[PDB]
Image (cartoon, rainbow over all chains, first blue to last red; front, top):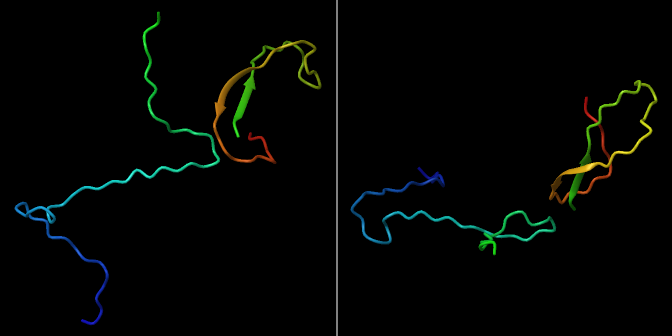
Length: 49
Length: 46
């Protein structure tokens, strides 16, 4: 008592409503540095006429 | 920024000491590493 340690826990049970049923969140943070670009979007191609 | 390596393997027949061969061989590029790191000193590994 009187030492409320900062780690707590969740109590997910499979009959909760929205807002309390757990969600899986991931963030894809992009950055532009002085290094050459290594990750980039896809570049689709066409046929060879 | 880019780091390039040129190389060519040649079968020398000339003896080993002080004989850099008197010929011509054009070194071909192998890879092009897209690093962003400055380089001032280097050392070989054996």
